[PDB]
Image (cartoon, rainbow, N blue to C red):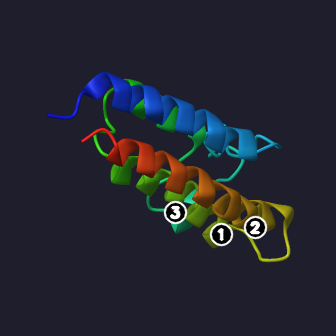
Amino acid sequence: EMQLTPFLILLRKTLEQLQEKDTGNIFSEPVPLSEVPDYLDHIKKPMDFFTMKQNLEAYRYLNFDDFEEDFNLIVSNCLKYNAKDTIFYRAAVRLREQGGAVLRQARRQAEKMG
């Protein structure tokens, strides 16, 4: 029923909006494992906005929940790995806060499609 192209257009816009909230671009690329050698010790599934864009374009997000789940991993991995008193941890809290409103608006648009 629901068409694929307008859904992917929405996800592209939503991803851009989420990225815009990450003003430091600290989530724009994968955590460099060369520089954080213990990262995979703690984090089961790394995620970042570039990997999300690739997934998007590989038609790997066919419902809103799967897209939102990867965004949430960006946040949750960061909260997990970094101490509370760091800029990184607080950036993840802020992203959670500001990304929430973005996601809620985008999900309503997706619901209007079905």
Amino acid type of the residue tagged 3 in the rendering: Ile
Residue 42 drawn above or below residue 3:
below
The answer for how far apart the CA atoms under marks 2 and 1 are is 5 Å
Q: Where is mark 3, residue-wise?
A: 43
> For this view, does 35 lie left or right of residue 66?
right
> For this view, does 3 lie left or right of residue 5?
left
Q: Where is mark 2, residue-wise?
A: 89
Residue 51 drawn above or below residue 65:
above
Location of residue 109 by image quarter: top left
Amino acid type of the residue tagged 2 in the rendering: Tyr
Q: Where is mark 1, residue-wise?
A: 79
Nearest to the observer: residue 85 or residue 17: 17
Residue depicted at x 44% and y 26%: 9
Nearest to the observer: residue 92 or residue 45: 92
Mark 3 neighbour class, 10 Å CA radius: few under 14, some 14 to 19, many 20 or more: some
Q: Nearer the viewer, mark 2 or mark 3?
A: 2
Q: Position of residue 80 (x, y in %)?
A: 61, 71
Mark 1 neighbour class, 10 Å CA radius: few under 14, some 14 to 19, many 20 or more: some
Nearest to the observer: residue 43 or residue 55: 55
Q: Position of residue 21 (x, y in %)?
A: 73, 46
Residue sticking out furthest to the bottom? 84
For numbered disc 1, what is the local secondary structure?
A: helix
